[PDB]
Amino acid sequence: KVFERCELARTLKRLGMDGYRGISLANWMCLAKWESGYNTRATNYNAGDRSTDYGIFQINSRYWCNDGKTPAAVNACHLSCSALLQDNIADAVACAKRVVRDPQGIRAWVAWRNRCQNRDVRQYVQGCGV
C-alpha cells in the first residue's frame, strides 16, 4: 500500500507515534517519505553486507527483523521481515518504536539525518488534522 500524506499522518497518530520518545509526528512522516515514499512494500537490497531494508520505514534485516537469508543477523523486533511488508503498519510501527528506544533515537536512520534533521518539517503534517 502507498499511503497518501495525511492518511499516513492520522494512521501513525492513532498508533501512538506523536511524541514517542520525544519524536514528533512530522519527523516520522519525513522519515517515511524519504525512506519509502510512504510505500509499505518498499524493499532495498544491500549487496555490501547482504542485508535488506523492509517496508515503509526501511527497517534493516541485520538487526531488526528475521528473513533467514541475512548472514549473522539478529531480530531485535522479534518479527518476520514479512510483517514489515503488510498494508497494515501496526507491526512496522511497533518495530520503529523499538528502534528508537536505543541510544540514537530517531538518528538511527541515516536518511532522517540527511533530509529531516534540522530541517523545516512542518509541511509533512499541515492540513492533516493531527
Image (cartoon, rainbow, N blue to C red):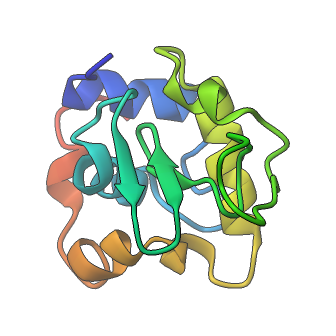
Answer above or below: position of 93 versus 112: above
**Residue 16 seen:** no
Q: Residue at x 28, y 44 (%)?
A: 36
Q: Residue at x 21, y 73 (%)?
A: 115
Q: Residue at x 27, y 72 (%)?
A: 116
**Residue 103 seen:** yes
**Percent x, y of residue 28:** 42, 53
In this picture, residue 109 sits left or right of residue 67: left
**Residue 21 location, quadrant:** bottom right
Quarter of the figure that contains the N terminus: top left
In this picture, residue 115 sits left or right of residue 27: left
In this picture, residue 21 sits left or right of residue 113: right
In this picture, residue 3 sits left or right of residue 27: left
Answer above or below: position of 10 versus 63: above
Quarter of the figure that contains the C terminus: top left
Q: Quick one: 49 or 53, which is closer to the camera?
A: 49
Answer above or below: position of 62 versus 81: below
**Residue 67 location, quadrant:** top right
**Percent x, y of residue 51:** 54, 59
**Percent x, y of residue 73:** 75, 62
**Residue 38 location, quadrant:** top left
Q: Residue at x 78, y 66 (%)?
A: 72
Q: What count of labels does the image hold?
A: 0
**Percent x, y of residue 15:** 62, 30
